[PDB]
Image (spheres, grey):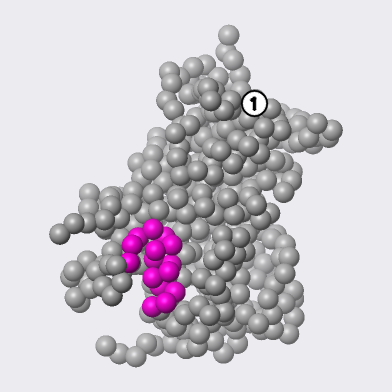
Amino acid sequence: VYIHPFHLLYYSKSTCAQTLPEPTFEPVPIQAKTSPVDEKTLRDKLVLATEKLEAEDRQRAAQVAMIANFMGFRMYKMLSEARVASGAVLSPPALFGTLVSFYLGSLDPTASQLQVLLGVPVKEGDCTSRLDGHKVLTALQAVQGLLVTPLLQSTVVGLFTAPGLRLKQPFVESLGPFTPAIFPRSLDLSTDPVLAAQKINRFVQAVTGWKMNLPLEGVSTDSTLFFNTYVHFQGKMRGFSQLTGLHEFWVDNSTSVSVPMLSGTGNFQHWSDAQNNFSVTRVPLGESVTLLLIQPQCASDLDRVEVLVFQHDFLTWIKNPPPRAIRLTLPQLEIRGSYNLQDLLAQAKLSTLLGAEANLGKMGDTNPRVGEVLNSILLELQAGEEVLDVTLSSPFLFAIYERDSGALHFLGRVDNPQ
């Protein structure tokens, strides 16, 4: 009779009303020669979605947007507490897709936990009250698509199994809409953890192309499945240019480090929060996407501001005043960040959600002990091609926000850009 505000994330009456044993396969060795994946061709498969989207589908985009964002903030709060000096960066859509991916490979106990965790209710014992994971991932593909229609967004999934663990094809096929660049590979995750922990990094360097050095504090030696999501965003922001020479960046009252600064001029929106005192600069990247850049009143107030502005479901601090003449100067960002999602779940006191007693039967021949669940982000902001000027010379906050879907694609903190 009635319907939830996230109603389009559920199984529909036709698909739920609508069998062979599941085929399976052992992933090839990590050594196997793998050609690089063309980042340009990926954009097409994003673009192909957005250009054929309907009015029925757009509602989901926003519905998944709200959830993914809320989850983003929960986990950025866990990242904040967990950890320092480089700051942080987090992609809520990627973080969301990772969770839904685990849902799509999870059976009854873990499934509903993950569903309700994401925010879609489970009135237990129904199928039309179960999450249509595949609908969601396509809907997430929408938000992802809208970000890049110049902006680049490649996301590739590493699915590193143990030697003997066969992955079920119907599960790996579920991840399609999340990304076509899924690489199931097999290796010894027992004898030597670091020699293998390198092997993944040397494999990513090959297939993805991106130098993403990501130190591991402690790797568990008894793990069968690794689920690593690697994302790469690259923003050549229009109206901005590289500046000659390297300029200093005040990292701390004592010391600083001279780095490249990109600068532009335009009619940007700019305000200063009456309540909490932080400057905000709303520089639009494309005709939709928006880079929000917050600076605190002073360097030491940043901790508070971050806890206040980002780490909250609300974006009530985002306003819209009359634009003005501004010469913005910020560092040429090459932000890199990496966090094991298991550690964040643990800091949120959900360590058993994907623990050793997690039921992920749908993933393979045997129940996989999912060791680490990486999220890795290379976010680059490069050059595109009276007048009071906003110069980001000290630590600042930033978020990259999509208007049409309403989703928040990246948020983070720049304490030091090398």
Q: Relative to 164, is 247 above or below?
A: above
> Does the image show residue 183?
yes
Q: Relative to 180, is 170 above or below?
A: below
* Magenta-highlighted residues: 108-122
The percent position of residue 31, horizontal first and vertical second, equals 64, 79
The percent position of residue 81, horizontal first and vertical second, equals 65, 52
Answer with left or right where residue 6 lies relative to residue 161. left
- Quadrant position of residue 278: top right
Q: What residue sits 58% from the left and 50% below the top?
A: 77
The percent position of residue 416, horizontal first and vertical second, equals 72, 41
Badge 1 marks a residue whose secondary structure is loop
Is the residue marked by circle 1 packed among few (<14), some (14-19), or many (20+) residues within 10 Å? some
Magenta span: predominant SS is helix
Q: Which residue is mark 1?
A: 297
Residue type at mark 1? Gln
Which residue, as the protein is rendered here, is positioned at the far top? 386
Q: Nearer the viewer, residue 360 or 169?
A: 360
> Does the image show residue 33?
no
